[PDB]
Image (spheres, coloured by chain):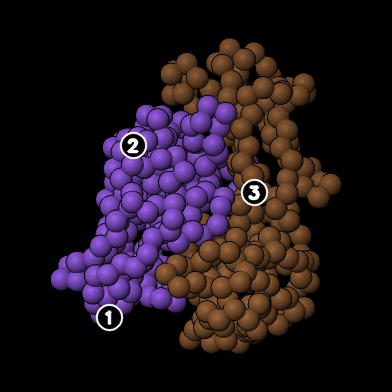
């Protein structure tokens, strides 16, 4: 084992990016490259240094001179955004590089869609209460979620995901606010407040509904 | 071309598991087959491979003496016996074909942990039109407090797929997961016609078909 990769690389949409793999082992094994998008299985994009599988875009190419393998992507599109892994067979061992996360700048921004659900009567009857804030179709994938009881910020009780890519290159995320029944009924309202790229969306929900 | 892994789940440290991959769509006995695994948030790590015949072939040093790869060419099946499992072995385990790893299955999750499994409470999210665009409504299911991953959600036993969004789970402070699935349907059809969340948490052998009524 050995192989070393850059953990992150960026490219402008349209520009060429080179992903470098440099572990020894390549020194004359022949290298494969795999693409992995989130929540998905790996695909081969380049095998034996230079060859490209039937359905891989022509803009994918590989190079390998002893030391170093290079995956080149010539005119980068939004959907080349994935993790890329280097592979080589030492002798009696398949070796993977630690992978490279490829970011494509600068795609157009998308504004978050925000849905807030109040606790169900069933959950309240089970003596618990969960507010559910759902956030979809936003790009870039960085949001800030803050909750408030009426207009006082609530600190304790909040669980928020980190944003994740969806089918259409955009992001989604969830925030959960766990309450006791009493504190759910004891305010006029609760609000999910989502900030994305300086803009803010606030959805509000009330026990008298 | 299909690689179908099976046999993953929750197991206690020191415990055993037998992973299984059933292949089809190609001539199984021509190919080196292999297992590659991926700890959550980590990279791809090669586990082991096996020649079309039976010699097999090396193992990653971290599983030598504990894991055994084998195959049954007459059942087109690849196997991975996992003994003396420890926390570090927690991963999605992928079945891959070939020296070049040209085909990967969807993988099976192995969780090695002391914590015991918990089934999820499933709460309905009554339809709302506040943030759906145009004469539609969003309704959903809250799948709260289960362990370990995963959970599958379907609507109306599979007959409803247009407009479904299942969100990726949160992992909470507690170590429990929760997620939500939301579906967008016509408001006109809000009551004639009915909506059922099918939730399934295999690790705890829980299923729940939750009817989601207008409030």
Q: For numbered disc 3, what is the local secondary structure?
A: loop
Task: In the picture, one chain is purple; tell me its letter.
Answer: B
The residue that appears at 58% across and 20% down in the rendered structure is: A179
Q: Colour of chain A?
A: brown
Q: Is label 3 or label 2 in front?
A: 2
Q: Chain of mark 2?
A: B
| B117 lies above or below B96 | above
Closer to us: A58 or A190: A58
Whether residue A90 is visible here, answered yes or no, is: yes
Pair 1/2: label in front:
2
Residue identifier under label 3: A163
Residue B130 rendering spot, x and y as whole percentages: 63, 41
What residue do we see at 28% from left, 52% from top?
B81
Disc 2 target residue = B14
Q: Quadrant of the N terminus of chain B?
A: bottom left
Q: Which mark is residue A22?
A: none
Secondary structure state at the residue bearing disc 1: helix
Give the CA distance from mark 1 to mark 3: 42 Å
Chain under callout 1:
B
User: Looking at the rendered structure, which numbered label has been put on residue B30?
Assistant: 1
Give coordinates of residue B88: x percent, y percent: 47, 43
Q: Is residue B209 rendered to the left or right of residue A81?
A: left
Q: Nearer the viewer, residue A130 or B97?
A: B97
**Label 3, label 2: how many angstroms apart (C-alpha)?**
35 Å
Q: Earlier in the sequence, mark 1 or mark 2?
A: 2
Do the residues at pointers 1 and 2 share their chain? yes
State whether discs 1 and 3 lie on one chain. Answer: no
């Amino acid at each position: 084992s050995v192989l070393t990769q850059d953990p992150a690389v960026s490219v402008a949409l349209g520009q060429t990016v080179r992903i470098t793999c440099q572990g020894d082992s390549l020194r004359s094994y022949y290298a494969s490259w795999y693409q992995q998008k989130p929540g998905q299985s790996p695909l081969v994009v380049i095998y034996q240094d230079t060859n490209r599988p039937s359905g891989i875009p022509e803009r994918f190419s590989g190079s390998n001179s002893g030391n170093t393998a290079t995956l080149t992507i010539s005119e980068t599109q939004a959907m080349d955004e994935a993790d890329y892994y280097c592979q080589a067979w030492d002798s009696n061992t398949a070796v993977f590089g630690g992978g490279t996360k490829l970011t494509v700048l600068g795609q157009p921004k998308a504004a978050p869609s925000v849905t807030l659900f109040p606790p169900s009567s069933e959950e309240l009857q089970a003596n618990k209460a969960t507010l559910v804030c759902l956030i979809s179709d936003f790009y870039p994938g960085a949001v800030t979620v803050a909750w408030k009881a009426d207009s006082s910020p609530v600190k304790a009780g909040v669980e928020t995901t980190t944003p994740s890519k969806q089918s259409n290159n955009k992001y989604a995320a969830s925030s959960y606010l766990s309450l006791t029944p009493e504190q759910w009924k004891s305010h006029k309202s609760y609000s999910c407040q989502v900030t994305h790229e300086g803009s803010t969306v606030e959805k509000t929900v009330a026990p008298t509904e | 071309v299909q690689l179908l892994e099976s046999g993953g789940g929750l197991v206690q440290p020191g415990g055993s598991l037998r992973l299984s991959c059933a292949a089809s769509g190609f001539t199984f006995s021509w190919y080196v087959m292999g297992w590659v695994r991926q700890a959550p948030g980590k990279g791809l790590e090669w586990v082991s491979s096996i020649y079309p015949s039976g010699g097999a072939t090396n193992y990653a040093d971290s599983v030598k003496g504990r894991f055994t790869i084998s195959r049954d060419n007459s059942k087109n099946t690849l196997y991975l016996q996992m003994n003396s499992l420890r926390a570090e072995d927690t991963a999605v385990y992928y079945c891959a074909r070939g020296n070049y790893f040209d085909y990967w299955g969807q993988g099976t999750l192995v969780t090695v942990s002391s914590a015991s499994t918990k089934g999820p409470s499933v709460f309905p999210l009554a339809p709302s039109s506040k943030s759906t665009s145009g004469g539609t409504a969003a309704l959903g299911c809250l799948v709260k407090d289960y362990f370990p991953e995963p959970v599958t959600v379907s609507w109306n036993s599979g007959a409803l797929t247009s407009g479904v969004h299942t969100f990726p789970a949160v992992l909470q402070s507690s170590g429990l997961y929760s997620l939500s699935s939301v579906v967008t349907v016509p408001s006109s059809s809000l009551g004639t016609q009915t909506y059922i969340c099918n939730v399934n948490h295999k690790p705890s052998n829980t299923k729940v078909d939750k009817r989601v009524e207008p409030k």
